[PDB]
Amino acid sequence: DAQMTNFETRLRENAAKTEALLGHLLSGEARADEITRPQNLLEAMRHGVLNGGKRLRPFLVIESVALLGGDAEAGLHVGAALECLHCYSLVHDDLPAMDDDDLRRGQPTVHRKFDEATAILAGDSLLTLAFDIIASDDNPLAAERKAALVISLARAAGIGGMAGGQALDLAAEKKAPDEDGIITLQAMKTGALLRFACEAGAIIAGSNQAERQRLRLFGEKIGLSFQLADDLLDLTKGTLVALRGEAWAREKLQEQVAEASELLAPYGEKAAILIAAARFIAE
Amino acid sequence: DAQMTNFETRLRENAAKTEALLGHLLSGEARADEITRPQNLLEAMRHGVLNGGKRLRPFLVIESVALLGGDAEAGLHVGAALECLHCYSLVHDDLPAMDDDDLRRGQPTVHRKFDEATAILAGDSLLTLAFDIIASDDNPLAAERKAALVISLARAAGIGGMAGGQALDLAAEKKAPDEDGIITLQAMKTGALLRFACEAGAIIAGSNQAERQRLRLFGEKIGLSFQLADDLLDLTKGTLVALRGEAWAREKLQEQVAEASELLAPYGEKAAILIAAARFIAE
Image 1 (cartoon, rainbow over the protein chains, first blue to last red):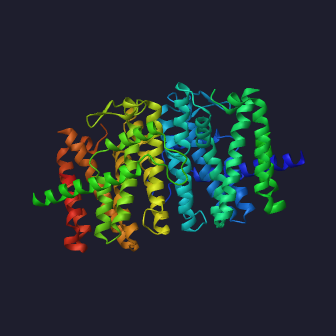
Image 2 (cartoon, chains in turn cyan, green):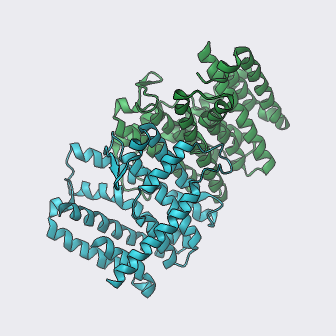
Image 3 (cartoon, each protein chain N blue to C red):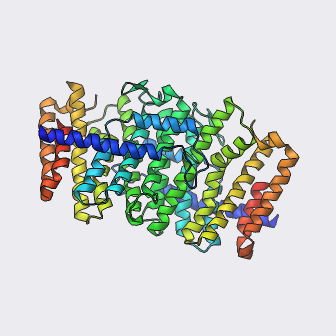
């Protein structure tokens, strides 16, 4: 209860910090190497970011970085980058060709407020900007760590990650997947960005391999829990809840929170915020 | 004539080298940090790359790198990355919401051979992969140079570059631009990737600022010539050919080739291939 308040409050704090930097990064002034920023496309990008939700992904980057003693400013920049990518994915998924949504969080979707062309280009531009934000000199982070993050984000986001998962998800609508197929498409469509968010803290902090693996694994448990909790919420069609039942799902959620917590045991009290996130997500 | 053969032959050689690496990079095997590569989406990506054209952009990267004595393997990887990005842009531009093309180079467009969702995701995945290819450890290039390239490519490709130019171009269809507007949207829509292709050689080679600027400027002249030559070809609506006339355009093309050639004068015979490219493009 007090711990759940701890998470909710930090989620809102980190959301506000990330949003402030995002507003700055989406300002109308051309940067070095940019010719001009067309105002309509930029407004569409801002709209896409406005509709992006509660900023869990930046939260996880920021808090992974804090756990491991990395540079909070680098954490904020990488969180913003990751959020831009998350938001691009929603702008494209909302399109008529994909999920065909007129509304997102009570507001018109980007293609409805603008048009489909502008939505396509806004998502394309937000995906592109994510990489700019990570690699830019105003992200105070060594080049080797920037390169590692670019690789990690691209792998998590692309053919073998998020985008591939979306392809598998759409294919699942016409041809029902089996359990192994569901686990795979979920790990890609939603798990990979959450994995990346946590692993990124270790990359940013310059952690050893063991610690980077630990945070990756933690991120995998967060994503597994995120997916189950969401499918349970909707319940109360290729879903593990559908195949295995609600009782199985609720026990597996409980298990994943316990596993997540055990992974961060070695950090003691300093892991409380991330452990609270696991519990919030899972319930 | 013999010089134009020199260019045409090297264009084909570099196209074949770049295509071989692209085929490898688009293989079905999951890489480290990828879960699996869905076969249908991967086929769509390959189709998008197959339809991409004559590989001028990789040619320029490879030859800029050669001019400045950089690592040809790094040149090949960065050229492949740039080509993936170029090809993504075509996959999205062909969509019904944008240019609405059923054919590209005599073949069905990606959304026609597959569907619109798959085309959207294929372009998204090719854009994402471009950044993976640049930053990956199998690109033999120092991290600092990789970061610089990620920034340069993202700036050239995004809101202040290619994507922004496409937005300005679509807006031009409903509201005619003036000359300054045309120059700007052209510099973004087509010039920026050609600028990047040439400047990239200097970044890869670890050139001093002066030399990097020189290759950037050369790339700007290539792009200016590329645009004019193309608009002239079509002639024989917001175009400089339309506003200034064919005679003005043909003289300006000639001027830009001369300027391009003068920029590379200090490299002597070693600049012959790039100078031939300027002449091929312009005529």
